[PDB]
Structure formats: C-alpha cells, structure tokens
Length: 169
Length: 169
Ligand SMILES: [Cl-]
Ligand SMILES: [Cl-]
Image (cartoon, rainbow over all chains, first blue to last red; front, side):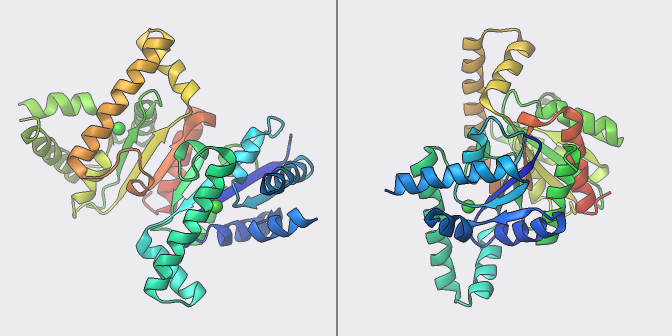
C-alpha cells in the first residue's frame, strides 16, 4: 500500500543498475538486483519465476525498495495492492554504451558490441518468455530515460524530481 | 540560439497537444501544432515537407517555442544552430486514449479504436517516409512520458524538472 516501489530495467551499458544503487543509498531504500534476486530463488524455470515473483511482491508489501531487472516492472504492475510503483527504463546510444562496457568490463570495441547484443537478447527473451509482453516497449514503463546526454547523477535526480512530483517524498 | 525549443510528439488520444499548450502558457513561450503548420505550408506531398521544415527552423531561430506533432523532433534536430532542444514523446495506456478520443471527438468506442488505428498508422508511415526512422521509437527522443498516472500539472512539472536539469531554465 503506502510503500514506494521503484523498478529500473535497462539496456546493458546504460548504468541502470548503478543509478539504482546510488538512488537506494541517497533515499535509504533497500536494493534488490539480478544477482540478489537470483540467489534469492535458491532460498522448473516456470517455478523459478513464480517463486521469484512471490518474493518480489512480499518485499514490496512490507518495505519501500528499488528492484533492478528481470521484468520487475511487469510483475509489480500486476500486483493491484501496490500503490506507489514507478517503472523506469534506462536506455542509451550504442556509442555511449560501447564505451561504458569497454571500460567497466575491460573488453575491446568488438567484444563490447557482442556483449551488449547478447545481454540485451537475454533480457528481452526473458521478459517475452515470462510476461508475454515486450521488454523494450514504452507501454511497460512510466518513465523511460534517454541517458545519451545525461550523467548517471542527473538521471538519478530526474527520478527524484519524479518521486517528488507524485508527492511520494 | 540559446532559445529553448521543445518538441512534443504523441499517440493520438494522449493529450500531447494539451500538455503542449499548458507549457506554452505556463512558460510564456509560443506554441505551434500540426494544423497551424498545415495551414502554414500552403502559402508535391514532398515539396510540402521541405517547406514546412524551413518554417519551423525560422520560428525556432527567431524565438523560443513549442512544436506539437509531425516529426518535429527529427526536424528541429537537424538544425545545427539550435542549441537547446528537448524532444518528448507523450503516450498513454490503451484505455485512457480510448476515453479521450470518445469524449473529445464525441464518438463510439468502436469508432474511437478505429480512428486511433487510422491516425497512428498515418503517423508511422509519415515518420518513416520523411526520416527513415521509426515513429514510436525511444532512441529518437530525449524523454518519453507515460501520462497514464500523471495529472496534467504533474506532466508539465516533470517537463520543467527536465528543463532545469538540462540547465535550460
Ligand atoms: Cl533489465
Ligand atoms: Cl506525433
């Protein structure tokens, strides 16, 4: 009900996750990502998903928090008990993404391109398989942010600009 | 030009124009839509576009202004002189635009659904024809906005939060 829930999904190379981290700290909200949600599942891949959804909804029911990745926006959009859900998609030019991935993963240009194609494929297919909707589709979000010309900080503040407007802060 | 230029493109029934006008007033800035642009060109379907484009650039060059509609984003983006552009895509869930089209055009659900399909199709083809690119696509905009859960003021306010972040205000 009351709790503020923010879901950030994103293009690989956008820094969506980092933007999620920053934002969790500056707001003091608990933070759950791909890995934590993955390891969570251990605490049929259609079971693994069902399990992971019920976990997501439980957290939300009992805390404010920020989820990153794994069709979190879809899942929580289904939960009619949640009132303060804000769904973000972070996206960016290839040129900027290749440079981030090159640096953050220490690979070259070619390798970086292939990685972006691959993780984005994974994210898209995951989403398609489980929601039946489309990961890269506006309709699935409240606010898609183009960070082509933003710092991750500006980006974080835009999300705060938003939480504030809604009166959730 | 350090002139602030905003371009709003949108799904039919999203109130992209509505939002365009509030901002126009709220900011003390001139406002230009399809129809003014339409009547503008006049005094090929393809000469027509090259003409129209030039008027927008001249308007943008003479003064700060808001454009609603018709590949405004892509066009004003060419103008190398424009130093302060913001490109926005307004959009909304299906229910809400159906309600809007019915109310506004004073027509049925059936006709409202149909007229949405019609107008949007015109907008995709128009866009791809004159830009080579795709109309309803994120990478072509700075800020897509989903108004599904935004009161009008909230929307206008979000666009200004953005302007402030860009330091255009
Ligand atoms: Cl994601
Ligand atoms: Cl449009």
